[PDB]
Amino acid sequence: MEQTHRAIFRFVPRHEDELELEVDDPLLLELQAEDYWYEAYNMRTGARGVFPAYYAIEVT
Amino acid sequence: MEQTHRAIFRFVPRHEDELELEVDDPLLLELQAEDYWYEAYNMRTGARGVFPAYYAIEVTK
């Protein structure tokens, strides 16, 4: 169960459900929801939460 | 009532303070906060709220 996605933009949470992203954070994406929020594990911070879909790219 | 910004990505609110964006929505940007959330008026919908700063680009006109 390794990285599915990589953060490409800085995201600072405003809401308690959100996942903080730094550029190049490795992400394990558990759910790509119909409202364009991704539920993920940040593999750098160990935090879980949601972020806006366009903040990450799919990795090989 | 002049547009400052344009939505470039679909943004569906999860929170009541958030602004729904469709791609190309004209935006009047009222506040660019230190945490990279923008407060805007959506000029298509008439809604107000906040969205993640990378979801919009500045229009130079």
Image (tube, coloured by chain):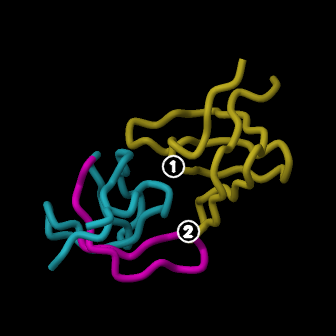
Chain colours: A yellow, B cyan
Q: Earlier in the sequence, mark 2 or mark 1?
A: 2
> Residue at (22%, 66%) from the top-left corner?
B42
Residue drawn at point x = 77 percent, y = 45 percent: A25
* Residue highlighted by disc 2: A15
Residue A2 image point, x, y percent: 82, 25
Picture coordinates of residue B40 (x, y %)?
32, 73
Instruction: Please say whether residue A2 is one of the residues in the magenta stretch.
Output: no
Q: Is residue B33 magenta?
A: yes
Name the side, left or right, on which A1 lies relative to A16.
right
Question: Left of B16 or right of it: where is A54?
Answer: right
Identify which residue is drawn at 63% across, 59% down: A11
Q: Is residue B17 left or right of residue B54?
A: left
Chain of the residue where label 2 is placed in the rendered structure: A
- Rate crowding at label 2 as few (under 14), some (14 to 19) or many (20 or more) other CA atoms within 10 Å: few
Residue placed farthest to the top in the image? A60
User: Distance of mark 2 from mark 1, alpha carbons?
Assistant: 12 Å
Quick one: quadrant of the C terminus of chain B?
bottom left
Q: Is residue B35 above or below residue B19?
A: below
* Residue interval drawn in magenta: B24-41
| Residue at horizontal 61 percent and vertical 66 percent from the top | A13
